[PDB]
Image (tube, coloured by chain):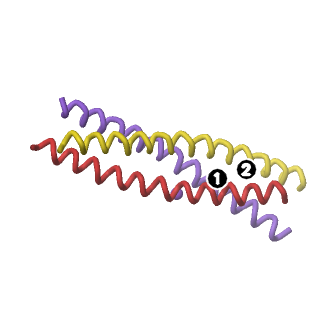
Chain colours: A red, B yellow, C purple
Amino acid sequence: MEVDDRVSALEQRLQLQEDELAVLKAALADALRRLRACEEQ
Amino acid sequence: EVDDRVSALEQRLQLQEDELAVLKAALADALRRLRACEEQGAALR
Amino acid sequence: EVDDRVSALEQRLQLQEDELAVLKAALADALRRLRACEEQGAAL
Ligand SMILES: [K+]
């Protein structure tokens, strides 16, 4: 049953990673749009 | 069931892996485009 | 047996953490340099 705490801990840390990835994705897609609007500029 | 939770974890980890691969290739493209614009900027100066 | 899967997941999660860290750091620099290019084109 100690195993249950390690699964729980993995679930929580993974959620923080998922949230961090979502944040990066939006920042990156924004950078790409700005860059594509500097290429054409 | 613990096996169901570990399975659900493995699925979420695979999807994270896909996303990271894609974001990494996308970042590489972004840096290329950035370097190009910087080189254009310095040349224009 | 399920502990071997859990251990393997912990080792994978940390490698993914490290990947994201490289991505985040390089993106931070790119944005800094992006702003600079925008600002030296708004003044121009
Ligand atoms: K970020």
Please provide percent x and percent y for residue C5. Answer: 25, 33
The amino acid type, in three-letter code, at marker 1 is Ala
Residue located at (68% from left, 48% from top): B30
Q: Is A9 on the left-hand or right-hand side of A31?
A: left
Query: Is disc 1 placed on a helix, strand or loop?
Result: helix
Report which quarter residue A37 is drawn in.
Answer: bottom right
The chain carrying label 2 is: B
Residue B12's disc number: none
- Distance between the alpha carbons at the discs numbered 2 and 1: 7 Å
User: Residue at the left extreme?
Assistant: A1
Asked if the residue at tag 1 contacts the one at tag 2, i.e. Cβ–Cβ closer than 8 Å, the answer is yes
The amino acid type, in three-letter code, at marker 2 is Leu
Q: From what the image shows, is residue A35 above or below residue B12?
A: below
Residue located at (37% from left, 55% from top): A16
Residue B34's disc number: 2
- Mark 1 — residue? C30
Of residues B8 and C7, the one nearer the viewer is B8
Report which quarter residue C34 is drawn in.
Answer: bottom right
Quadrant for the C terminus of chain B, please.
bottom right
The chain carrying label 1 is: C
Q: From what the image shows, is residue C34 above or below residue C12?
A: below
Q: Is B36 on the left-hand or right-hand side of C32?
A: right
Please provide percent x and percent y for residue C19. Answer: 47, 41
Quadrant for the N terminus of chain B, please.
top left
